[PDB]
Length: 149
Image (cartoon, rainbow, N blue to C red):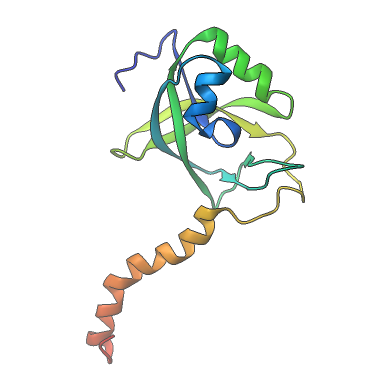
């Protein structure tokens, strides 16, 4: 972080604002974006009736992006825009750069028990096969056990 976030703000994006092009249009510019991980939350996916939302999931983590260096008018404007169906909450995200943790705002889905948002996110599906990446180092370990794989 060198964007200076005192009077400037940093927000973790998820749905509509996860694209910098819409950011340039909706406000003017696009704050420095960083890949961050929000542990303890999960993003769901859909478009049409409902959109990608963020809900507290103990078994989940959301890899998304953080917009840092946004001005206060726009920060309230984001609250105005997202506030229609979301609430602005503070969360802890981890830099996918290092392993640094930060506290940012994000918009969380207010209805915690919702069947409309129910869908497996790309990352959940990938998290499954992503296991295999770890398993690869274990897969060799079977040789010692009985059978090299």
